[PDB]
Every structure is written in C-alpha cells, then in structure tokens.
Length: 108
Image (cartoon, helix red, strand yellow):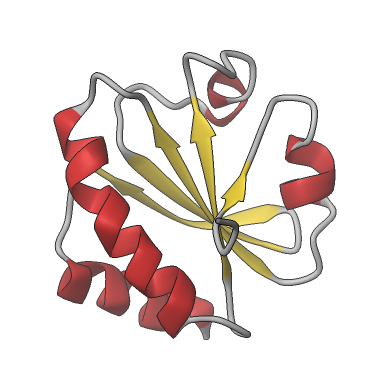
C-alpha cells in the first residue's frame, strides 16, 4: 500500500527535504471533498510517473506542523519539490489531464 509516501511532521525532512529528485506533496484532510476527489488521480500519477517522481501526502490535521511552513492556506494544495526546494504550486482540485500538464511542464 505504498507507492504514495504517507508523510508525517517528523518524517517530512527525510522524506521530502532530503530526497534526491522530485516529490509531489499533497496537503489534504478527510473532511475535504476536493481532496478526496483528487486521491484516485494521485494513485494513477504515482504509477504513471514512477521513476520520474514520487507522490507523498501530508494530512494537515494529523500532522499540523508542516503546512504553515509552506504558507498553505486552503486544501488541496499540491507542492512540487525538486531536491528539497519548491518548484511549482497548485491550489484546488484539478483533473488528471490538468495534473499531467502541471507535472510535465514543471519537471523539465
């Protein structure tokens, strides 16, 4: 059950900040319907982008510490990290096609 890294506040440094390569971090919560709408889409991307990218999820209620560090203000927010640095930001639900395009464009 791990293609997706399931992050915590304590593991966020190792898992994201010190990863060699691109991580796609999904800031989300259980009550958030758009967050849940995109979850299946993230599963497909995890598979599709395997070897180019890792997908990780931080649940902002269970892990309240990390989101303020990135000025997160609404969910879902997708932050693309490249080797510990944020390259791209996407706020709100989007389709698979839209996510593919956001990824393809920011991964170069």
